Each structure stands twice: as structure tokens, then as C-alpha cells.
Amino acid sequence: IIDGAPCARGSHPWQVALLSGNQLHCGGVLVNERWVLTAAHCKMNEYTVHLGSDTLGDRRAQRIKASKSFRHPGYSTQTHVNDLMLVKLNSQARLSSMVKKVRLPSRCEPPGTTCTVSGWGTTTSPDVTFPSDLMCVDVKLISPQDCTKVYKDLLENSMLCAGIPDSKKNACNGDSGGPLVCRGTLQGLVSWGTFPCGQPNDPGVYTQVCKFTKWINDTMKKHR
Ligand SMILES: COc1ccc(Cl)cc1C[C@@H]1CN/C(=N\N(C)C)CN(CC(=O)Nc2cccc(C(=O)O)c2)C1=O
Ligand SMILES: [Cl-]
Image 1 (tube, rainbow, N blue to C red):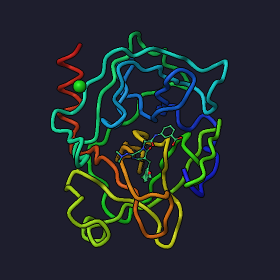
Image 2 (cartoon, helix red, strand yellow):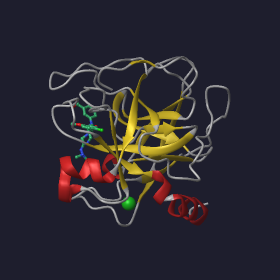
Image 3 (tube, rainbow, N blue to C red):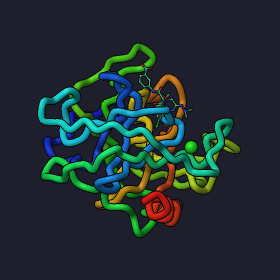
């Protein structure tokens, strides 16, 4: 997260990180006691999942292994269309004050909407700086018509764009797969943008979650 600030404590209880060892690989969100949603480009053979603390490495955090994960079948490695994946926890998260399910959307929030994206990703770019503390930053949804001016053929109608005009405020390496939430609901998963991070007027791009709820529900149901 570039040009952001520490998340207020205990207010991102649905945020997780996917770790490789004790090293951050991706962000993600808790859908339920069994499942984490995150980006497809985070796929690994095995994951260690951190839940229930704004601070990485916290004594109080839960660490659960996840040995199985399920990418959206329409995911493209070449173009990153359909960049989402469900991650099955090897055991059920203990829900608590610091561990809640995210509110999945029932609606696509429109352009102009104010959102918060959260993550333990680099706070600088290209020179990297990693925070223990979960960082948050507010951006507005940006219309396909506006975002296509910048990115053209790269965009799908299931990708959602967000930023602030003339603003470095954005996500970055480590934030991948993590929550963009707007008006209480999960509206995006951090997918891609430009390098280095935080170039003014290059919006961050997100998997638009409101277009994949059927898949998310069917897949959890199918893999009960
Ligand atoms: C330049 O990066 C941007 C730009 C805009 C957004 Cl919204 C988000 C990012 C973060 C990227 C997103 N996408 C990426 N690949 N795409 C093309 C599928 C790369 N990525 C994964 C990544 O770099 N993870 C990572 C994890 C841990 C350590 C490091 C490291 O560089 O040290 C990197 C993103 O997170
Ligand atoms: Cl898969």
C-alpha cells in the first residue's frame, strides 16, 4: 500500500495474508471458517495462512495451513483475466472479534464510490519497504470508460479500476489478492497495475468480485 496509513486496529478482521514460511506472498480475505478468497496469480502448492491480527508475526494471530486451492477455471496466465482463487484451509478458522467473514457483495458499487484497500505489501517502489502493520488506503472506483483511456485492450468488464487522480495512493507488491471493500462489502481483489507502484493517474486494477459470487458459492458448495 503506497501513501496509506496504518489500518485502525481490529477493523480488518476478514483480512488474511498468505505466507510462504514466515514470508509474505499474498493478501486474501476470509469468506468463511473454511475458505479464503485471493487472486489466482497467488497460486502455490501450499500456503500458511495468517488471520486475526493487524500485525504479521503476532503471538495472537492464527496460523492455518492450506494445502488445496482452486483457481477460477477461466483464469488466464497471459492476460490475468478472472484473477481469483479459493483457498481451502486444512482446518476451520476460529471466528472471533479479530476473525470475521467478509461481507460478500450483493451489488456492484458504481464509479465514484469510496473504498479502502488493505495490505502488508511494500510501502515503497521500486525500492521495497515491508511493514509488519496492516496498511490501509482510500481510493475511488473509476469507470471502465475512464480506466480504458489508460489501459485500453488489457481491461475486461470483470476487472474493476480504482485510484485517486494525481495520487500515488495505490497497492503494491505483497498486496496482491487482498481486499478492496466499499460500503461494507467486498468489491475487489487486488490484481495488477503499473510498475513502479503508485504512479499518479495509473489506477490499480481489481478482480470485480460482484461478477463472481455464483462461482464463489458454487465452488465452496462443490468442495464441501
Ligand atoms: C506493480 O505492482 C502493482 C501495481 C498495482 C496494483 Cl493495484 C498492485 C500491484 C502489486 C502486484 C500485482 N501484480 C503482480 N503480477 N500481476 C501482473 C499478476 C505482481 N505482484 C505479486 C508480487 O510481486 N508479490 C510479492 C510478494 C512478496 C514480496 C515481493 C517483493 O517484490 O519483494 C513481491 C503484486 O503484488
Ligand atoms: Cl487450480
